[PDB]
Image (cartoon, rainbow, N blue to C red):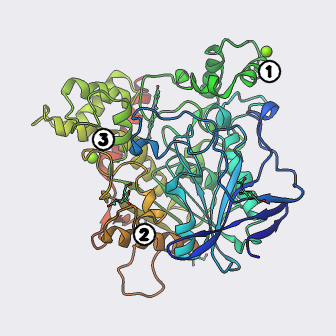
Amino acid sequence: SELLVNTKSGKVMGTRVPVLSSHISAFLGIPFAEPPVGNMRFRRPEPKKPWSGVWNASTYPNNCQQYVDEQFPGFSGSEMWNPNREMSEDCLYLNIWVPSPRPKSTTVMVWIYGGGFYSGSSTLDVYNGKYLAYTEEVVLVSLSYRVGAFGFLALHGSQEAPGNVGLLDQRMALQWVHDNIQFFGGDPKTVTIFGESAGGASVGMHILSPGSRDLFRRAILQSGSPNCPWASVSVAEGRRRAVELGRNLNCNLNSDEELIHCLREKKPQELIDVEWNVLPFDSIFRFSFVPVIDGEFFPTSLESMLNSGNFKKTQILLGVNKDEGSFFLLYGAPGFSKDSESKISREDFMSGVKLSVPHANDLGLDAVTLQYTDWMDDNNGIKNRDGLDDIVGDHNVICPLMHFVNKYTKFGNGTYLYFFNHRASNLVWPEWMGVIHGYEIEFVFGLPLVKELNYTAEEEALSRRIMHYWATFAKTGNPNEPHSQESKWPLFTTKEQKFIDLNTEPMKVHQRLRVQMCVFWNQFLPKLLNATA
Ligand SMILES: CN(C)c1ccc(-c2sc3cc(O)ccc3[n+]2C)cc1
Ligand SMILES: *[C@@H]1O[C@H](CO)[C@@H](O)[C@H](O)[C@H]1NC(C)=O
Ligand SMILES: *[C@@H]1O[C@H](CO)[C@@H](O)[C@H](O)[C@H]1NC(C)=O
Ligand SMILES: *[C@H]1O[C@H](CO)[C@@H](O)[C@H](O)[C@H]1NC(C)=O
Ligand SMILES: [Mg+2]
Ligand SMILES: [Mg+2]
């Protein structure tokens, strides 16, 4: 009976599930931490006390408490990211997908979902590991971590609400997989962590954090870097927002201990309803509770760690999508609509810019406009629309990831960069939105292979190709075949900075991803902002 496994925590009864005219084992809801409920709220996570009897891991677990997106009711496009299980503070569980027959010492891949550190679920249809597991024969694991105030509230100095506890949950999970994935046919020495958006930043933060380095082999980052503008705040800013939440719930603000009691007596929803009120500025692509540069989990500043090489050195595979900013513009920028091509007016554009670089002074905003405005056609509604897409995209995702790539590729042991620019055939979103943030995930997980999902033959091709690169990487540290005639995915180097694009057409090798616009974001602007504040 391959559905029965004994782990250093207890026994787990899996379940045999269908996967494209075949089957594989599935262990859903394996707990790896004690319920972070009641007194535990905001505290670090403590390990799950070994359970007696046989734990039933045959159906996905509860999701963590979070904001739910109700901007476009009954619109799968947006609702596909919403929790699809009962929200609950008790949500520290993980999922395993094992091939059949159960292999031994095979490649493991742990997925870290994204969602800006404020939302997420390891049980979305798009994160079903069965396909990947089955097709490439690897033990796919999808973990979970606390999000929102519940996983990142940061009153640095306290021991009850230190912050980064969310990142800690992902660790304990990575730990558990470490001391247990073998029983499921996994090889704890060939673990590859991969996540998108906040998940990507997470992977990269584990590459930085010393207390995580020894828990995985290589790593993959999708549309998200650890040094992202939105991926973290200073202990000061975190404490401010922490107090701010309390003030928003009529809490005793005198001492940390008082504040913590108050926030612990409030119902999950009471905290969620005012979550957004703590953000310092009116803006987009910014979230309240996120990783804090504490001095522990993160030894020193991120730029300093990257510049000195103070971080796990191994092979990494990462990339971005053609239109990282469209999603966020649609939800919080003026002029945009889901029912039209959103031609943005000049007045709206200025608005949109300020909502994208909220920390920028008036001069900084001008620098941004000049940099992204065509003065030979400034009224073109289409150019302004795309302009913002690139602005939000480059500032929040591409450029940060680019900065990281380079800084990393100076101490690492191999880098593979990609440019996902394929516009799905069944996409439910408008066309101006192009290749949307986070929409490259369905291909990494092989959802196109499903015929009922109505994907074009060529898209199943791509999905299969991507899954191979990905799994192949995890297993070998290189996405290319050992010796095939297929075109190779160049290795990214400080000198040539090559990268490929991921789409249906035949591979093309490009050089210096958005190098121009990124000099602006990584050098000039910051330099300007600092000298003029
Ligand atoms: C699915 N994606 C990418 C997404 C979904 C939702 C949001 C936001 S930003 C924001 C700001 C605010 O003050 C209130 C609500 C709110 N919501 C819901 C941003 C991106
Ligand atoms: C949990 O395992 C039991 C077997 O004892 C099974 O009958 C049940 O369907 C599983 N999940 C549920 C429905 O709670
Ligand atoms: C990785 O390390 C090995 C052995 O230490 C070395 O031979 C190889 O050149 C490195 N690969 C890259 C591309 O850095
Ligand atoms: C593909 O998607 C639809 C959407 O629900 C599904 O019902 C059906 O199996 C497919 N559409 C058809 C019948 O062409
Ligand atoms: Mg009280
Ligand atoms: Mg664009």
Within 8 Å of ligand 6, the CB of disc 3? Answer: yes
Is 75 placed above or below 489 here? above
User: SS for tag 1?
Assistant: helix
Q: What residue type is disc 2 on?
A: Leu
Q: What residue type is disc 1 on?
A: Glu
Q: Quadrant of the C terminus?
A: top left
Query: What residue is disc 1 on?
Result: 257
Residue 181, x across and y down, in percent? 73, 67
Q: Residues within 10 Å of mark 3 (few under 14, many from 20)?
A: many
Which label number is shown at residue 449? 2
Residue 122, x across and y down, in percent? 59, 51
Residue that appears at 56% across and 66% down? 130
Which label number is shown at residue 130? none
State the separation of the CA atoms marked 1 and 3.
Answer: 43 Å
Quadrant in which residue 85 is drawn: top right
State the separation of the CA atoms marked 1 and 2.
Answer: 52 Å
Query: What residue is disc 3 on?
Result: 389
Quadrant in which residue 128 is drawn: bottom right
Foreground label between 1 and 2: 2
